[PDB]
Image (spheres, grey):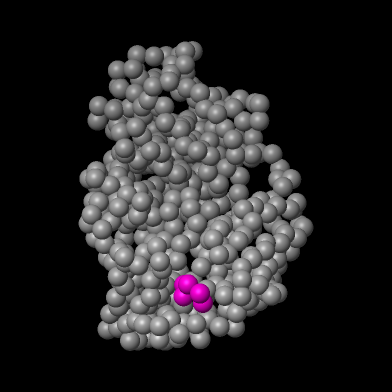
Amino acid sequence: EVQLVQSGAEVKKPGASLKVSCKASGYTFTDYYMHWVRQAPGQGLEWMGIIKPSAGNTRNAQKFQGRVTMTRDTSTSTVYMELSALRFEDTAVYYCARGGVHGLDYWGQGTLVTVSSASTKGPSVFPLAPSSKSTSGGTAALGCLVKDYFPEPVTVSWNSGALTSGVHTFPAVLQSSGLYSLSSVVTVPSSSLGTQTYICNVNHKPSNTKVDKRVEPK
Amino acid sequence: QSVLTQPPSVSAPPGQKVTISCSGSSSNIGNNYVSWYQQLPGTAPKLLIHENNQRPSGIPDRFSGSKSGTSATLGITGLQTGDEADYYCGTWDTNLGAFVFGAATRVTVLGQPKANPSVTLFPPSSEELQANKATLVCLISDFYPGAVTVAWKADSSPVKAGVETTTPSKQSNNKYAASSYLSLTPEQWKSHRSYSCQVTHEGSTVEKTVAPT
Amino acid sequence: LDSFKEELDKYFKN
């Protein structure tokens, strides 16, 4: 299977430079072009450029010609995209895509790059214990509160990905303090609260922090 | 985006056919391969159509693409709620020497059943209270249409400060999700008898209350 | 150069 794995989300200061990596697997690295596409929050797709992994030829779009530099490492089947003179307006999700079938047939997961003068901040995870009066028949709601982190994003899984039924990770809210907070809740059978173990796995790549918080019955 | 012109939105009742046109010129569409891309809410873009009419594996046959002259068209038969997403037209422009995407076209299915919101309110955790903080978490989910208003009350009086509410967000099952947070100090939490989260949706209100006890 | 652009024009041409 063709897979394109990108580097994690990061905070960058204005004027700095960042290099996003894209490791290619499942296909011959030197047989296909590689594209880069950026998408600002709530905006459309913007093509950035294309690289030929065999000889290293690059061609960038007009908007990004003065600040983007794309390289590649054939030994590791990895394409790099460097954005210099970073600015607040560069905050976006950056994708690599394989240039098969004369289009962009396989995409990476995307890398959310935030440009800000504020520093990164790890999250504070608190349990949301399932209450008794808040239950709904045979189902109960329990979750984790991920408070006061910067920047986005954070990924929440339950039982290391072994629990996906009923899981709902809500979008984050931007507080007046400039920090984000969100909640992830899984609907669980109300009778298996005492037997089943419920762990929320919170990952904040920009701070290089992972928290596995255990949610107990109240 | 400017060289490729897409409609901002297309709509059709469930089970009907929708059509998205992508208009360009001889420099891009009239002479180069056209591809279409689908972006489900909260997901990365994926290839829907390549080489103007070919479907990769995993794409339902309800999706169809074609090209005529300097325009390309994406067709979706039997429109289901799972097709609601942003659709992008893409091709190569020989004048610019660049790959170009059209502006997003949002597909919306009309006549969707009304969903009354489900409200779940969490009191501050003991861990947070031991950490000199307190936050009330009100979670609203499975509502349609996606317009909710949240009101908070200390006992029976409104609270305006410390209230942060998200914009309604599209869930994966379509429908909608929202969350509202009320930030308190541990003093104000234990000092009151009850705190309330009221959610108004389509002229009807669902209210849940929690108490320090 | 324009050679790479000409390569891409040839590739994407339908």
The front one of A26 and A65 is A65
Image quarter of residue B15: bottom right
Towards the viewer: B43 or B9: B9
Give the residue drawn at x 61%, y 75%. Answer: B26
Q: Nearer the viewer, residue A49 or B60?
A: A49
Q: Quadrant of the C terminus of chain A?
A: top left
Is residue A161 at all visible to an observer of this figure? no
Residue B101 % position (x, y)? 53, 65
Q: Residue at x 64, y 52 (%)?
A: B9
Q: Is residue A18 magenta?
A: no
User: How many numbered discs, if any?
Assistant: 0
Q: Is residue B91 visible?
A: yes
Give the x, y percent position of residue A120.
24, 47
Q: Is residue A90 left or right of residue B63?
A: left
Residue extending furthest right? B16
Q: Taking B159 as reference, is B187 left or right?
A: left
Q: Residue at x 23, y 51 (%)?
A: A13
Up/down of A77 relative to A122, above or below: below
Residue at image location 60% in from the left, 61% down from the top: B5
**Magenta residues, as a range?**
B94-98
Q: Main secondary structure of the magenta part?
A: loop
